[PDB]
Image: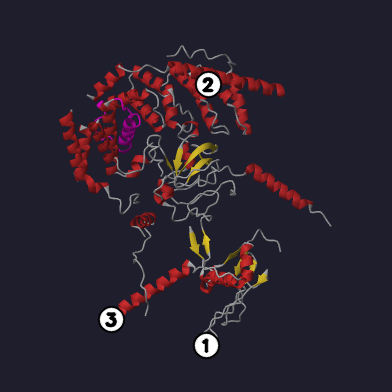
Amino acid sequence: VRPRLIAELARRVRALREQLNRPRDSQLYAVDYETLTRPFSGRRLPVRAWADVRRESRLLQLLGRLPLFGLGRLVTRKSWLWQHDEPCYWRLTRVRPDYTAQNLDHGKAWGILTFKGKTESEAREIEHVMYHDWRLVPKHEEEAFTAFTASVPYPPLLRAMIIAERQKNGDTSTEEPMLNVQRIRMEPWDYPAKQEDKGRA
Amino acid sequence: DSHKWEAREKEHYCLADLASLMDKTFERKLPVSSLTISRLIDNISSREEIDHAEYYLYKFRHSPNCWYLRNWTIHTWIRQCLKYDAQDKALYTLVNKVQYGIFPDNFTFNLLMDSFIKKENYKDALSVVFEVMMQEAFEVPSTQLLSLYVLFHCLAKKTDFSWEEERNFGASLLLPGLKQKNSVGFSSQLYGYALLGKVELQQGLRAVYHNMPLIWKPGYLDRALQVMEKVAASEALDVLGAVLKALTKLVEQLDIEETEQSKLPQYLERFKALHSKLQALGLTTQLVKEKLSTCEAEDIATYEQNLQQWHLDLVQLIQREQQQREQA
Amino acid sequence: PPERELSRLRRLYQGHLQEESGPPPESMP
Amino acid sequence: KAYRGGHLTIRLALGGCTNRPFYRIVAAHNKCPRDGRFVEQLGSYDPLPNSHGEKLVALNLDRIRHWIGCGAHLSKPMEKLLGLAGFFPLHPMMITNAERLRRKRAREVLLASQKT
């Protein structure tokens, strides 16, 4: 057995580089508005976010015009508003503002969420912070804004099989077999994920 | 109201050294404590010095500690400004807002307003008011003062206003307009609503809410009407606006949800009815003046307490620093 | 669907839409 | 072989010559090739209709279930097949396709009527 020291060294170097000269996200969450592309990467944005990109704002930028970086405030995603009747928002507990950006914006921020008026204990790191679908909720009409008030057949063949099995066993049992989605929840597709689990470019 | 503050407590009185240190920190791309910034702010004694401090503040804002820019420091800066010139530099900082990171949601604003009043300057005052509105404020009794100022401005400002300005005016009217105690407040609110309605109708719904503490929901005229009706249960400008409306891209509103351009005559009728009701039942500047003359019992004890707290915090910080030094 | 949903959908996809039928048939010769 | 955490999949596979497609339903690694190795072969499917109009499909349901339990995903064709069998529900895509077809037929009928 020979040792591949050089490879290891290279890996270490790479790691170091990643640690150090990593792009502070002023650079790589930038947007050229007229051409709808990006510095650093160079790739375009998708069509279904062009108008949105143009005529609405970042979360962190929005925050930037508040004392304490709006640490005890509500905030909403425009998409959610469009979609649901129900009140849908986060409240903040923290900000990680990327300092390198002239007129501070872009970075990270987080707190408690509530999708369709259903809160959660503990504060995750919140997704879509650098998207442009965001709006700030004023303190006047804040409490006005926040106002809120099983079993299914098996598929044809499986059920039949089950019945057959039962018969074989001995019992007749006219009670039909059924599966219950009381356990199986259906958190929607527009429900947000977690920035702890995602990797940054 | 200056001599209560001017017991600042002593620190070092050399600025050049501090500046050098700051530069070094920035050269290295290392963070800086708030304490140093505070000290710098305290030290200033010239317009050049003020300028330097401004720059330093900006630098701090663009650093690993954007936060930690404590209220106390801001207050000190404001005081310094007041002492020297005030009405150009502080205002500029406020305008910049995000760059100098000052966010003085406090009695500082009130003080500034008072100062402005003392030496006329109306446009600047208006600007300041607008800035305050843009920041989420108006728990304190400076609201009344702000309203008064706005009214005064209006008394001069009587033309077509224009896009941004109208919106700003509306904002000013609205958020300070939370005066349940008197009908003047209600009137102000109504006026604000009317302005906002006008803005909506001429230009767009997005034009209203984009940057302001204001809510996307379409019914602003309706809201105003409701408010007016509430008063009755318990204006000329509005009427004019309505008349104008009556006289001869993306879509946030729905197909089912009805367009407010096609609800006008009904709205007008409703307004008329409301007016009639008011008449059956049974100037603004004067009212505001009267209000000012009454009320206004101050927040001075609280201020003192806050100051004390700040001092304590500073002391704690100093102690911490000392400990660190010892450790080193 | 209820009409509200339809409206929402329309709003979402303003420029990119198609006119549609309600239910389909129940036969096909 | 070691892959970057490629999930398990119950998937089809071409076991035919040119113009005769024959299929092999198979529990395999996501990142494996199509006709490359697999974990355990399951019920062969024939798409070409044999003597007297049958399009026969094998399924070791017993082992399919096991695979599912062990956390192996299903490709869309597989899902469709399952639905057809009655083992799974009819895949909603299939239903939509059917609906579309019906609509088309209706349109055609209308056109014919117009012509006549």
Q: Residues within 10 Å of mark 3 (few under 14, many from 20)?
A: few
Q: Position of residue B250 (x, y in %)?
A: 35, 51
Q: Amino acid at mark 2?
A: Ile
Q: What is the spatial separation of the Cα atoms under label 3 and label 2, in whole angstroms?
A: 89 Å
In front: label 3 or label 2: 3
Check if mark 3's residue and mark 2's residue have beta carbons within 8 Å. no
D85 over B208 or under it: above or below:
below
Q: Position of residue A166 (x, y in %)?
A: 58, 70
Task: Choose the circle earlier in sequence order: 1 or 3.
Answer: 1
Q: Which residue is mark 3?
A: D115
Q: Which residue occupies 69% across, 44% down?
A: A16
Q: Amino acid at mark 3?
A: Lys
Q: Nearer the viewer, residue A153 or B17?
A: A153
Badge 3: chain ID: D
Q: Amino acid at mark 1?
A: His
- Element carrying mark 2: helix
Q: Position of residue B256 (x, y in %)?
A: 30, 53
Residue D47 sits inside the magenta stretch: no
Badge 2: chain ID: B
Q: Which residue is mark 2?
A: B41
* Residue B50 in sight in this render: yes
> In the image as oriented, which residue stretches furthest toward the bottom?
D51
Residue D60 numbered mark, or none: none
Q: Which residues are magenta?
A: B155-181
- Element carrying mark 1: loop
D77 over B135 or under it: above or below:
below
Residues at marks 1 and 2, common chain?
Answer: no
Q: Nearer the viewer, residue B84 or A134?
A: A134
* Residue B83 in sight in this render: no
In front: label 1 or label 3: 1
Check if mark 1's residue and mark 3's residue have beta carbons within 8 Å. no
Q: Which residue is mark 1?
A: D52
